[PDB]
Image (cartoon, rainbow, N blue to C red; front, side, top):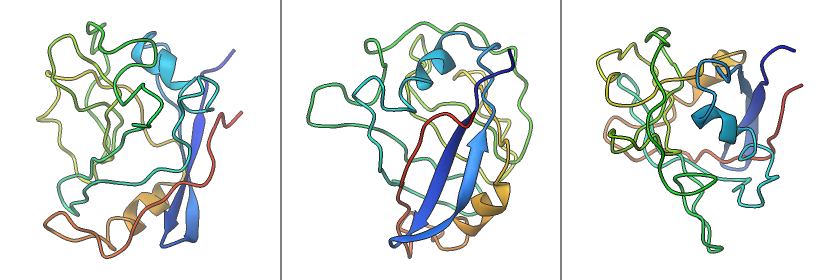
Length: 165
């Protein structure tokens, strides 16, 4: 009944901002996004819970999301390392769609980005799946405290996570 949605919080130097959730096409990608459900509630035990960003570029994209811990899992696959690509029936739309940035060839991975601009010229190499349910108003704020080069005037941190519904 209905697709599972996950919420996310955006922090800035310890100060809260808002809340952004993603519907996620668990039906279009019954595999890659099928694991994210467990890596979003910390149920797998590997969940990072309280991470940050790596790079931010206002005008092109953002990228910089992982969950590498001392344990021994790292950012890649919740049930292994890499997995073949299921499909990309999902078209490239929206100024900030959800997908993933990995090697490309049979390696969906866990890496992902935000994207503040329409960049449908990346698809074809990775498996796209996701979107901006609600809270986009925040996705813009973070795209103003950064810097056109890599470094960010501020620092994005996570507070809590899990399943919206």
